[PDB]
Image 1: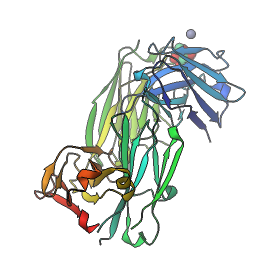
Image 2: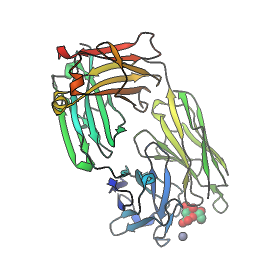
Image 3: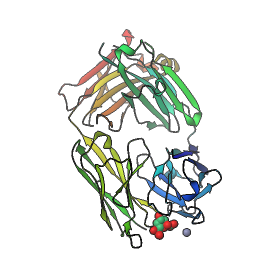
Image 4: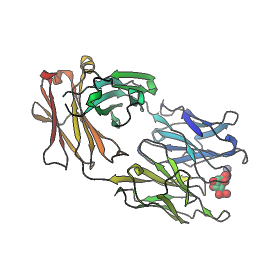
Length: 218
Length: 219
Ligand SMILES: O=C(O)[C@@]1(O)C[C@@H](O)[C@@H](O)[C@@H]([C@H](O)CO)O1
Ligand SMILES: [Zn+2]
């Protein structure tokens, strides 16, 4: 299994610095160029730079958009890749992805991480309030929800019954208002399964290390 | 300095139909020594990381369904899906690697399907929220098509527009529908002054609005 995992993402003030890391496994690290790529929320992919393999002496290159400001490095004893970002500004808010690049032959980014979200803002971290949305009232299916209100920055994650309820889930894109986000999630299950069998939304807010479970009760 | 442009910016196609999207570079990506075009295509389904589909213009990565074909040479490339499936909903990106790397701005592929009415659900403010001083009323308009839809909130029978925010999801990768939430936020003091809370959904699928309501006195 090839694995790439970014970490380091979160809230930083304008003018501040942040380093991301990309941990890799499942392939011969030194044989590969590694690239970083970013994507502002709802926008296009932007290639940022790469660091070459051992054959090419681990040299770096950068897009004009970040050259002189971002720094890439790698730890070949640990199979790790880094991105140091300096003098951050609003245009830098984005999900950052590390991708496995050129091996001296193939021209492709064969593997990507899950990405880590960086928010550049002076607004303060605020944990969510999490509220149950229990159904009033007699059909074959029933819809429940959780309201995740008043948090900053993105992201938050919402699962239902620890991820065991995956079909019939809708988590709605957050909306920003007064430097705070709100989102909600619905899940739709058979009426034979609630309240007889429990339904619980699990909310995480990494920026505040918030972990919440709200069981939906009649 | 290679400029990559993609067209169309978006388009919608029904399952089973062909689609073609295009990618143009400001300079040739045909490498003279290797005799190949350094041009790859990536698929990014909603909320996921990009995935490689095609590299060297026309080489299909292992695991990629055969309905995906890359074509072209020099400055003009295409990605064609012979017969689209619900799960092909994505943004598609082309990328050059002839000189460093540069992504095009993407083409957003939407799936067209039969019109479908929304399933509507309304929820009162929780006691936890009310105890804290706030009152959010939530309405889910779920699994409908097409995307355009209107919601009207009524308090004791009168329309309220202030304090309503809406949010659509991305298209569903299984049934090709959209869903939307509408959230009316009020103070506890104003919430407690009225009884009837109504969410009214108007969609092209019916001349009759779908109406859901609850009464505070019935909670
Ligand atoms: O700049 C390079 O290190 C590199 O080898 C990257 C390759 O992807 C490719 O762009 C190559 C050019 O084809 C020149 O050989 O340069
Ligand atoms: Zn150089």
